[PDB]
Image (cartoon, rainbow, N blue to C red; front, side, top):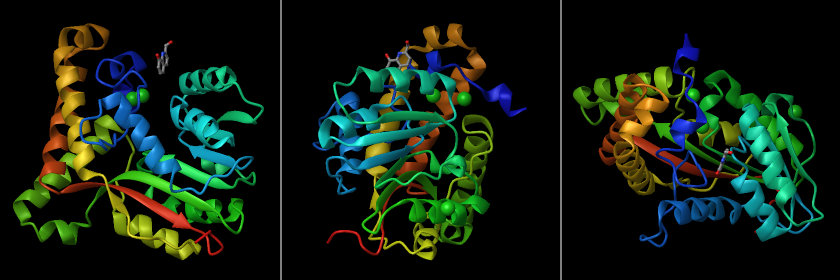
Length: 281
Ligand SMILES: O=Cc1ccc2cccc(O)c2n1
Ligand SMILES: [Cl-]
Ligand SMILES: [Cl-]
Ligand SMILES: [Cl-]
């Protein structure tokens, strides 16, 4: 049933930047191109992890390998990537083999559940919404236990508010936003579940992590979703013939919809840092 919502990588290519990054860009400075801003977002994440030469970085949901490659090139670190996409696995192996380094580069076709190797630092960019509510305790325990005393993790995730907080903005918008979230979790990311920032923070604390004030990327996702929407819209004919009018309509609704609800502050995007007790000052 969810398989009906499986879409070819070719489609995403028609609205994403050349890196094919499927997550919030970081427009600092404001007038970066989408491509440059996707690199700036990778740097935002990596710059919080206190990476030193010879450390191993684990990337949970390593995508097309852009984060891992930047990490090797900027920080001279070993990398391990986890992905569930064969196509992403293939791309990543070739991206990493392409790098002129002596550092260990490994990509694994598996989830974090199956990963139990010591690593120094963890990065996870918009993979966490594709886990499940009941999995969050196990995820933070795993991350805590596989890292040394000075371990750090960043998790970037799209975020909803608890029904109670949404009701604070009036019942009309709340029920309306609840149904749009349902649509995303059914047809865009089937079986997904949007966490709250509060959940991301408190599950981290329960596992023993120090969690500073999460960074909001709301304004950067608005700009990202606007460019994605405009780009998909300009490639409508091309997009339709690669999939269907059904799929184009679905994704235009997704992109225009998120832009709207991010603007109305019924959705957020959180970059949460998790510091182990022995993390550097
Ligand atoms: O060969 C096709 C292909 C597949 C994945 C990609 C990811 C990022 C950039 C690219 O050009 C890609 N090209
Ligand atoms: Cl899909
Ligand atoms: Cl994709
Ligand atoms: Cl464990």
